[PDB]
Amino acid sequence: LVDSLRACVFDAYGTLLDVHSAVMRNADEVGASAEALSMLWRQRQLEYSWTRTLMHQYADFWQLTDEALTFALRTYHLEDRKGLKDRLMSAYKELSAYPDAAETLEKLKSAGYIVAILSNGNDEMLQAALKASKLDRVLDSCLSADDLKIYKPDPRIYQFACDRLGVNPNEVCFVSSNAWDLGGAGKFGFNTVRINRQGNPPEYEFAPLKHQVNSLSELWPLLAK
Amino acid sequence: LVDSLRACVFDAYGTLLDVHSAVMRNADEVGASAEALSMLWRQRQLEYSWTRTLMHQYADFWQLTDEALTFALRTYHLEDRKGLKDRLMSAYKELSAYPDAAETLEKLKSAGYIVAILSNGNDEMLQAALKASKLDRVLDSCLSADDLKIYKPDPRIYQFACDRLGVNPNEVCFVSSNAWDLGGAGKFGFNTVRINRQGNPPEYEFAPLKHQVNSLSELWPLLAKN
Ligand SMILES: [Cl-]
Ligand SMILES: [Cl-]
Image (cartoon, rainbow over all chains, first blue to last red):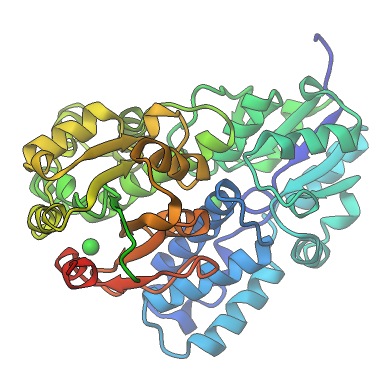
């Protein structure tokens, strides 16, 4: 209503964790298609999450990441799909965190916010990435779409966060770099803040943002209690 | 695929209609980003259709096409987005048919099949494209997502086709170039045939295809009746 925020709920893949880094770290082994491969990998991973939910054929996020990567490597006819695939999936398992993630989650946790992740990622892949990047120690809760077998932006995933954290939608500040996820969270009723790193155009305008910043570290002035 | 089939149900955008022609015909006006622009427009159009159904914020396919193009034009920071938008939307309204589309639908209609389209596209945009390409005369029925306000691959849209056409799922041969649409249709229970023109890798393998061909013309030996 007037002084309401109790919880900062973060997206993982694209917001706290850098999805470009799995291919970036291996770009020389991939060759000059690396950027195109990386974009195709990401678009199919997300496509599969959406279409499989619509058609009621769920599989977990690691499996979709794998299928999307296989499809992308095949599309680009790469040499040594197999060794390349192993390296790229290992890099994905421990996806690099954005440089300001750890510090800004610490700062929010110290201001006394419930600090949580809400992610499409299943526990195994998510916990592996959060452990490697040290983000797991600065979280109250990490909530997985794999508990529901239903992906974002179905409202039941945002409802899961509310129910687990014991908060109402208007007591949540929902932070994401993914416009579709901000669209679903905003429609659902979270207060949404976009991390817009590259000044990408607006989308999903029927669910306006509360705020937009260009880095995680700009969340702290904004959310300082 | 044994013929106790009563209906051939076709995807429109990507299968009968060439989604690439809207930018290709205006590539000089767009400049060197034309292909990357074309790919983003298409990807976001489809993204919008999936995510809006998942979050219960339907809008029609023309609106999504417009929003996706506006987004793609801004992403590429294009000069004269206003003029380009008008040109590209007009081109989309009358997308080119693939070369074998009209003739193959006529052969199928001659063999006594119900020949129908089942499309995400709303009637206004789809009818314009169908008329411009003379595909109108080779069709029994044109079914739209806009009737139910629910996009593919949600099973209710495939069920809508069964309902309107008076057929069971297993009496349908469902034809598409879009792997997600074949996945949805196949899981629903239609007999699925992929048009894979460029030999793209397989996807959605939990819903196997009945057949794959590289051209709509190849549907003729697959479906011709005694
Ligand atoms: Cl970025
Ligand atoms: Cl093609």
